[PDB]
Image (cartoon, rainbow, N blue to C red):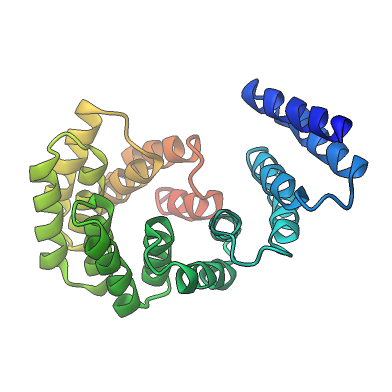
Length: 256
């Protein structure tokens, strides 16, 4: 119908204006007008994303769950809800959606990459390795697949393999600063604090560091018995949205 279509049209124009509150209401209104419309699962997908971009994470999960209902093997819905589960720390639920996705399309690169990372986090290193290899088998040119391997090797304790990969990637893209952040983290986990600082100094001089890099520099400053300098960095990372619980515990280690 015409009313249903005009409400969907207003939702699009509101999304284009950044008015997610109004876009959400137009979608909800459209669905009250035609509750039985079979194209509603598409509206529920958009609503889920609009709700997620507002931080209404529990609501967004309900919208994606509803959208998925009659379309259990929809790549978009599975990819968005698995990503949302990850954000909610629902690791088994996120993995299960990537498993549904990847049994359907074993060559879906975003799903492979995200599952790969999840497997690293779950200490499941052999399965992470196989997911990054799958990407490189379909896309030899993939940089993030090689980075996946670099992060994996570091978490496994194969520091030299990890360092070889980061050195290669950095030689290839010598100004992709986020690579220096990964390599610095590897050097810190290796006990190579002065070497890590060299990488950290490069990012601070040439770019805008992440909150993670302020924690990393703070942790090194801690090890260098410079508690006041460390706290300044931990406070800065907190002001940037780093985990408030963990940032709270790090700050206690600076208050001698």
